[PDB]
Image (cartoon, grey):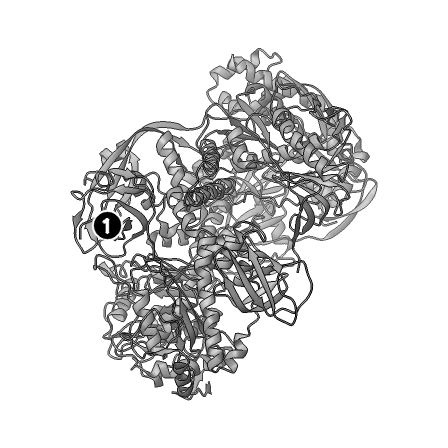
């Protein structure tokens, strides 16, 4: 009845419109407004959801699987890369497409996104791709400007942008593999390019093309490659040595890759990528047993014993590397917000963060154990259930559960000395 | 003439006009019914800064002192960084405001302003006060202007009694096959049970001329009946006064207008009274006209229904403001009762039921007498009182026979019943299902049927006065008045979470504690759906029934569980953090001041949800609950200190009303729509109850009497924190050494625990139970926990909590006595 | 359109096929209540008591519920004035003009808007007296309102007081907006944002918003 109720309804309808590009806060607010509306007016056309399907397909069309034709207006060329895809929105964080979660991102990229969104009100979202822990902002859509001014803004803000190509087409030409390769080379990058995003001045919808063909090859080994501190990217080769590209270890599990077998792969001019859509508990243990029991799921990477230590605390703390526990408290006092970050989280929070421990596996494994605790510190432990040992992550994390308990006691006495 | 300053309240109500007021209907001793006008207002308390910050002055304000403001939010914590409970001490002011001066920040808003009026003036609801004429300006004949209730209700006087005019009435209407409708189904006959101030149990059963023949009308007039065709011609004293529908409804309108003190009906405010309303509007143009005593409003008859939830039920009411608490029996009784049926047959069956002794045998007519000593001193008197009118009696609880001739003197009855002759020692006389097919008699309506159904209806409407003094509803209502701090009009009208707010507000005004909430509640109830399964069905021994004296109402005194003594609720998602927090808490908050309580994990990801409560100060809810059980004990003591029968009425009613209000607190703690909401409070109260039940079961199961010492399966150790009692599971038993018996716990649901004894000697069961009660109360229980033995069940055949039968033996009896034969759930 | 004979006036009740499952019980109730209803003169006349049954509902989504016909100038069309002289419809036209900006207009009919069915709860009232005839009408009123809310997306009621407990009599929960009656004091119906909220809730229901301007006649 009130205009305030009208504004609440308008906000809820807008949230319903922007629900694929949402986060936990947006979903919570939408649910709260839905509750208020359905209580007040006894019925509402929209209900509550929890999974939250995230998609940008409204701004895109069906992909071109064959040569087609173009003609009118000017076109802006932007490439499509390989790796995990995330979307950054207004007052929201990076969320994985399809399985939207709260991913952890650095502060440089976060602050760059914050400023590039605070510059003006007219940005729908920021599109990002993660590849070998290399943040790449691929595109950004808006109803007023074009991914050029925001691209220059991002380039001068410090985060990478792709070289946007602006071209004009006059005659009727059949866009084929040759012209696709020509524009791909026109970008001049060594990163994987899977598709091309070309836009027209005025059209909000952006359509993409992808030319490919099927190929089959033998798999000789799956091996991790060092691409960070305690971070190794698994990879496979061929008989000729061809490099098959992978987004995530989740993709490897989802592909049911078998050692010393044959696989299907859609090969590009420059690179080739193995195809998904080949259970999870079976594969997660079979691949580890193939590679070795001494391999633990280090997030989206596979690692060795991961003997960790003090400097592994420093690196995630992003403090000066030190092998002395005494140095672990000196600069913290000079650090205005590092002490804030450490104090705000729990001891268990820092513990799980510093060792790359997956949440669910570790929590279940812990919920299958027994513990002796003295002076707020673990003094012994013992497995309560060995059924969790069926899961390879459980047993692997237990192998260095000594690492966890050591680092955990270190963190706790770190809190104690930070009091001092 | 003059005004008698000594009055007693019999009814309060609130106005309906633009200028709204409080009109009180009091009674003097000498026989006066006096009305007093009280200017109603609106009531609010704000912090003194808000009070000083409002420029347009409030009409009247009164401070209450510097009262600490307590936040009562529930905030879970995954670790021990638990913040101190928010506590701001400030001075509040109580404002008397006439207009709804709605304020963005005003406190104590969930109550009802009439309760605030009561407490502000200190005016006791049922209290008899010596009113002040100088504070009572006469406005109307019987209505007076009372501007200052505080200085008017100056001198209170002891309770005395008064003549009260309990009118009753109930009718019947000729339905065809479906339900009787006002438009199509006419009135069959009405029957009233007028009781004036004189106590004259006047009767008149009016019969509809219209549905009968004019020749038949002449026959009935010749057979005793008096016929009148207007409103002016009526005389009360006759029984069968005959008239047509217009005349009947005009006289009824003359009746319900009358400044009655009470009015009672079964089902009435839904079907019957509305039926008079609609039929009298359909035939005449005069709606039933109620008026205020001061002659400033005149509402018309209004049927509206108010819902409740805590089984979907609806309760009808009428907001007449004449002065008469337009009561009802159906809704109120269903509020007080959890019965197999609430059909009037069943309520009469389980209200008046006296045993019979066979006098005359032969033919289908048998004569039976019952004296005061036939069954019990008291059953005979009331049953003979309700055998003045009734027609059918349920003999042996299945032989529904019609009264042929009833002879009653004072303390007993002699009745001839149409039940077949059978040589039997005795019989149970009952008013069960009636054996008259009103539908059949209507289908073949005539004169003799009209008279007999007129008597049927006079019975159906004089049962109202009998139930009105059996269920003591006048006494229970006057108890509700001074208990819930409500008007008598609405003692059984509101819902529980509303009524409890009276004494809660009294307590809060005493402890200067205000409960606020700034956060939104969450969507989960208090119950998890607990299911109890008996160990066995057929029992070959005696079962010692042990109860609990107010399990939850006492638990909330022991652990001080409350919203302001709940300092935090700690959870952890995994076993390691579980144990870490467990030991951390066991270190930080040391017994005995605190208490570590295990609850159910509220969320699927959680597995351990520690609730930590501080017993440093008895809070508000525990303090109130101790006050309730203490005052119930006080009144149940005063029930056997006095001899005046009126006392054995008032004190019984007050005791029972306290039992009802105190027993319910556990619900209103966990009810999201209650003023006592603290989710951990309810969760931990249930948990503590569960721990006590399991503890007692462990105590009694496996326990064997060793010669002269009782050797339990488990020691007598406190379950909650460190204990200084002799936890020895060997206790000296005050029985001879030749006794060697073993106990096997068999059932306990929430407060009653079944105890099996390894024998069938019920007398030995009673003796052992007598010693056992003292044993429990002096060794096993602690602090304030106390129990009292209930019964001994030999040949106990139970299926669940409700379907069970046995031979119950009283502790006042022995093996060679009369046991109590219980059979519930029999169809 | 189908017609059905009652025991009394009009002895013929025309309705659209949407109203078909209501006719039997409607006939029974009216045959019961008809003469005692006839005891007074009605605005509209008894002959007009069933022109609100021929209107189809399958294309009607927002039901604007009026509690009773006018005591005078009863025509059977809810809220309608043949000369556009009723204060209520004047306020309706004022608010719709303020929402839509229509400065100049001559009249406003709620019956010429697709998706909107003007409706009456109680089919009749006594001359110069409101809701006095509700007693004979209760069954018919509830029957019609339930059959209507079987289909209509939005239920709007003019007069908070007169629609105090419309929720109870209607079983299936439905989008319900309870607004001021145009006879509200201090021009609170002017402050009412009912129609914009109605359109918003329609869109929330993935439903076509009401073009209230179609009711205007120039």
Quadrant location of residue A384?
top right
- Provide residue C7's location: percent of width, then percent of height: 43, 87
Instruction: Say which residue appears at 53% left-offset and 15% top-offset.
Output: A418
Q: Is the C terminus of chain B in the top left, top right, bottom left or bottom right quadrant?
A: bottom right
Quick check: can you spot residue B762?
Answer: yes
Q: Which residue is mark 1?
A: B36
Chain letter behind tag 1: B
- Provide residue B686's location: percent of width, then percent of height: 58, 37
The foreground one among B105 and A139 is B105
Relative placement, left or right, of B231 versus A299 is left
Q: Relative to B574, does residue C90 appear above or below in the rendering?
A: below
Q: Relative to B481, does residue B789 appear above or below in the rendering?
A: above
Relative placement, left or right, of C83 versus B656 is left
Relative placement, left or right, of C84 versus A96 is left
Q: Relative to B555, does residue A24 appear above or below in the rendering?
A: below
The foreground one among C177 and B156 is B156
The foreground one among B670 and A216 is B670
Instruction: Say which residue appears at 76% left-offset and 50% top-offset.
Output: A215
Element under label 1? Answer: strand
């Amino acid at each position: 009845t009130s205009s305030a109720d009208l504004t609440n309804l308008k906000e809820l309808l807008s949230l319903y419109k922007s629900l694929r590009f949402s986060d936990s806060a947006a979903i919570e607010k939408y649910n709260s407004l839905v509750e208020w509306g359905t209580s007040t007016y006894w019925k509402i056309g929209v209900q509550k959801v929890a999974n939250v399907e995230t998609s940008i397909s409204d701004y895109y069309d069906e992909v071109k699987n064959k040569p087609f034709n173009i003609d009118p207006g000017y076109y802006i060329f932007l490439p499509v890369y390989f790796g995990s895809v995330f979307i950054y929105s207004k007052g929201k964080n990076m969320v994985e497409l399809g399985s939207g979660n709260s991913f952890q991102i650095p502060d440089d990229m976060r602050s760059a996104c914050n400023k590039v969104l605070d510059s003006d009100n007219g940005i729908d979202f920021l599109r990002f791709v993660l590849l070998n822990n290399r943040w790449i902002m691929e595109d950004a859509i808006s109803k007023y400007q074009s991914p050029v001014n925001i691209f220059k803004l991002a380039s001068e803000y410090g985060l990478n942008i792709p070289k946007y190509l602006e071209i004009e087409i006059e005659e009727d030409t059949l866009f084929d593999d040759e012209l696709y390769s020509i524009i791909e080379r026109s970008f001049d990058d060594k990163f994987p390019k899977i598709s091309i995003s070309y836009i027209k001045l005025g059209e909000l919808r952006r359509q993409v093309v992808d030319f490919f063909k099927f190929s089959f090859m033998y798999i000789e080994s799956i091996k991790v490659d060092r691409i960070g501190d305690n971070i190794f990217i698994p990879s496979v080769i061929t008989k000729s040595g061809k490099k098959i590209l992978v987004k995530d270890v989740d993709h490897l599990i989802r592909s049911k890759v078998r050692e010393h077998t044959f696989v299907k792969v859609k090969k590009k001019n420059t690179f080739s990528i193995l195809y998904d859509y080949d259970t999870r508990g079976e594969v997660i243990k079979r691949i580890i047993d193939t590679i070795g029991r001494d391999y633990y799921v280090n997030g989206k990477y596979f690692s060795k014993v991961g003997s960790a230590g003090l400097k592994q605390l420093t690196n995630k703390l992003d403090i000066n590397e030190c092998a002395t526990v005494d140095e672990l408290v000196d600069e913290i006092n000079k650090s205005g917000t590092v002490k804030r970050k450490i104090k705000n989280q729990s001891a268990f929070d820092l513990s799980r963060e510093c060792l790359g421990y997956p949440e669910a596996d570790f929590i279940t494994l812990v919920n299958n154990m027994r513990f002796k605790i003295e002076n707020c510190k673990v003094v012994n432990f013992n497995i309560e259930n060995t059924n969790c040992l069926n899961n390879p992550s459980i047993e692997t994390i237990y192998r260095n559960f000594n690492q966890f308990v050591s680092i955990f006691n270190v963190v706790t006495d770190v809190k104690k000395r930070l009091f001092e | 003439g003059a005004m008698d300053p000594d009055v007693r309240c019999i009814n309060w109500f609130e106005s309906h006009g633009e200028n709204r007021f409080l009109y009180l209907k009091s009674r003097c001793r000498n026989g006066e019914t006096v009305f007093i006008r009280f200017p109603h207002y609106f009531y609010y308390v704000v912090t003194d800064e808000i009070y000083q910050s409002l420029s347009p002055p409030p009409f009247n304000a009164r401070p209450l002192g510097k009262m600490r403001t307590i936040d009562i939010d529930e905030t879970i914590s995954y670790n021990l960084d638990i913040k101190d409970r928010k506590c701001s001490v400030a001075d509040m002011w109580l404002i008397e405001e006439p207009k709804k001066r709605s304020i963005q920040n005003a406190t104590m808003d969930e109550f009802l302003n009439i309760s605030w009026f009561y407490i502000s003036n200190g005016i006791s609801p049922d209290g008899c006060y010596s009113l002040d004429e100088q504070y009572l300006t006469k406005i109307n004949n019987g209505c007076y202007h009372c501007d200052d209730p505080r200085n008017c209700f100056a001198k209170k006087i002891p309770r005395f009694d008064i003549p009260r005019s309990y009118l009753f009435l109930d009718i019947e209407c000729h339905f065809d096959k479906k339900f009787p409708s006002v438009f199509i189904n006419p009135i069959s006959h009405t029957s009233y049970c007028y009781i004036d101030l004189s106590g004259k149990r006047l009767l008149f059963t009016l019969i509809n001329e219209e549905m009968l023949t004019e020749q038949e009308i002449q026959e009935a007039v010749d057979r005793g009946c008096l016929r009148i065709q207007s409103l002016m011609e009526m005389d009360y004293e006759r029984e069968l006064v005959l008239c047509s529908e217009i005349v009947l409804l005009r006289i009824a309108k003359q009746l319900l207008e009358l400044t009655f003190d009470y009015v009672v009906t079964f089902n009435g405010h839904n079907f019957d009274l509305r039926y008079i309303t609609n039929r009298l509007e359909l035939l005449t143009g005069e709606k039933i006209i109620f008026r205020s005593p001061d002659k400033k409003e005149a509402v018309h008859l209004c049927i509206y229904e108010r819902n409740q939830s805590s089984m979907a039920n609806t309760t009808f009411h009428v907001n007449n403001n004449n002065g008469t608490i337009f009561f009802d029996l159906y809704s109120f009784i269903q509020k007080s009762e959890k019965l197999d049926s609430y059909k009037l047959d069943s309520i009469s069956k389980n209200a008046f039921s006296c045993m019979g002794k066979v006098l005359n045998r032969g033919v289908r007519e048998m004569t039976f007498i019952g004296d005061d000593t036939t069954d019990a001193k008291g059953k005979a008197a009331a049953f003979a009182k309700v055998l003045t009118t009734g027609n059918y009696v349920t003999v042996d609880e299945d032989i529904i026979c019609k009264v042929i001739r009833k002879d009653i003197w004072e303390n007993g009855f002699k009745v001839v019943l149409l039940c077949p002759t059978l040589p039997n020692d005795t019989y149970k006389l009952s008013f069960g299902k009636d054996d008259v097919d009103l539908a059949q008699m209507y289908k073949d309506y005539n004169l003799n049927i009209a008279l007999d159904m007129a008597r049927y209806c006079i019975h159906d409407a004089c049962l109202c006065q009998y139930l009105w003094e059996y269920y003591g509803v006048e006494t229970k209502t006057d108890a509700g008045a001074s208990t819930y701090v409500l008007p008598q009009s609405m003692v059984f009208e509101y819902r529980a979470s509303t009524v409890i707010k009276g004494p809660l507000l009294k307590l809060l005004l005493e402890t200067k504690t205000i409960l606020v909430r700034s956060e939104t509640k969450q969507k989960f109830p208090y119950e998890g759906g607990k299911v109890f399964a008996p160990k066995q069905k057929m029992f070959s021994n005696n079962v010692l029934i042990f109860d609990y004296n107010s399990l939850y109402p006492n638990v909330c005194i022991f652990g001080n569980l409350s919203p302001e003594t709940l300092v935090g609720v700690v959870v952890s998602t995994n076993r390691l953090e579980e144990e870490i927090n467990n030991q951390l808490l066991l270190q930080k908050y040391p017994p005995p001041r605190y208490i570590t309580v295990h609850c159910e994990p509220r969320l699927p990801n959680l597995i351990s949800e520690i609730a930590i409560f501080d017993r440093s100060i008895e809070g508000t809810i525990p303090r109130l609950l101790r006050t309730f059980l203490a005052e119930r004990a006080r009144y149940k003591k005063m029930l056997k200190q006095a001899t005046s029968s009126t006392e054995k009425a008032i004190y019984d009613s007050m005791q029972y009303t306290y039992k009802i209000v105190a027993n319910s607190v556990y619900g209103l703690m966990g009810f999201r729509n209650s003023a006592l909401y603290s989710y951990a409070s309810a969760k931990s109260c249930t948990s503590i109850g569960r721990r006590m039940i399991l503890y007692l079961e462990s105590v009694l199961n496996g326990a064997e009497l060793s010669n002269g010492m009782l050797r339990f399966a488990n020691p007598l150790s406190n379950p909650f924190y460190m204990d200084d009692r002799d936890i020895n599971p060997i206790v000296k038993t005050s029985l001879p050494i030749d006794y060697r018996f073993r106990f096997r716990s068999v059932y306990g649901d929430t407060d009653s625990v079944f105890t099996e004894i390894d024998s069938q000697d019920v007398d030995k069961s009673i003796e052992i139970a007598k010693e056992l009660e003292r044993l429990i109360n002096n060794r096993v229980l602690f602090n304030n926990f106390k129990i009292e033995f209930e019964a001994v069940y030999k040949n106990l055949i139970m299926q669940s909590k409700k379907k069970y039968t046995t031979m119950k033996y009283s502790a006042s009896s022995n093996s060679k006595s009369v046991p109590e034969r219980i059979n519930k759930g029999t169809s | 359109m189908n017609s059905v004979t009652v025991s009394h006036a009009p002895y013929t009740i025309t309705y659209h096929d949407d109203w078909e499952p209501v006719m039997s019980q409607l006939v029974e109730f009216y045959n019961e209540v008809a003469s005692w209803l006839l005891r007074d003169e009605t605005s509209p006349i008894p002959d007009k008591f069933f022109i609100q049954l021929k209107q189809p509902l399958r294309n009607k989504r927002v039901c604007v519920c009026g509690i009773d016909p006018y005591p005078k100038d009863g025509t059977g069309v809810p809220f309608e004035s043949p000369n556009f002289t009723k204060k209520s419809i004047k306020e309706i036209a004022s608010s719709i003009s303020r929402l839509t900006g229509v400065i100049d207009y001559k009249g406003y009919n709620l019956n010429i808007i697709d998706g909107v069915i003007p409706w009456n709860y109680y089919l009749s009232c006594k001359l110069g007296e409101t809701k006095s005839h509700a007693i004979y009408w209760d069954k018919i009123s509830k029957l019609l309102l339930q059959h209507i809310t079987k289909h209509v997306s939005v239920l709007y009621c003019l007069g908070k007081t007169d629609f105090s407990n419309i929720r109870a009599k209607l079983e299936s929960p439905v989008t319900t907006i309870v607004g001021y009656h145009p006879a509200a004091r201090d021009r609170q119906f002017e402050k009412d944002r009912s129609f914009e909220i109605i359109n918003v809730l329609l869109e929330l229901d993935n439903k076509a918003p009401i073009n209230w301007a179609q009711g205007f006649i120039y």
